[PDB]
Image (cartoon, rainbow over all chains, first blue to last red; front, side, top):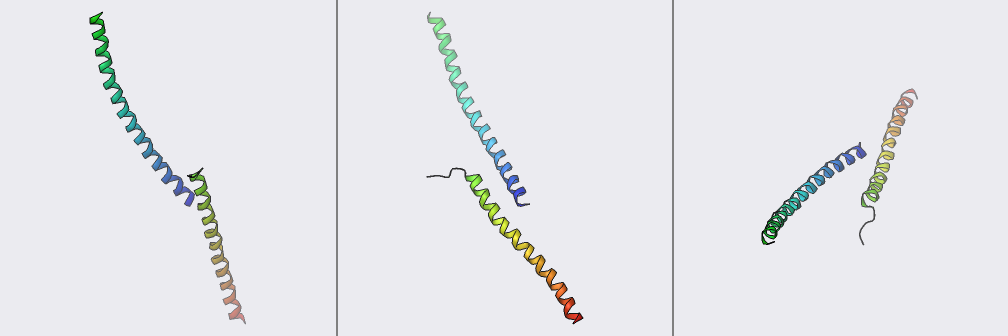
Length: 50
Length: 45
């Protein structure tokens, strides 16, 4: 029973950690999209200035 | 400075402290198994 409840608590905490990693990934992806917008604008500006 | 395998080195402690609790459990069982036949022997004598 003791090893059972140990494994159970560990799996719950691991699920929480995976959710936190998902949050980190979402934040970084938002930042990357924000950068990509400016990159596309610079691309259009270069096409104009060419 | 930190711990190499914390989860494993802590599961070892959990197992070591549970082995003693289990070994102490059978002691109660054998003690009561002795108490019953001891009372029977008292009555018979």
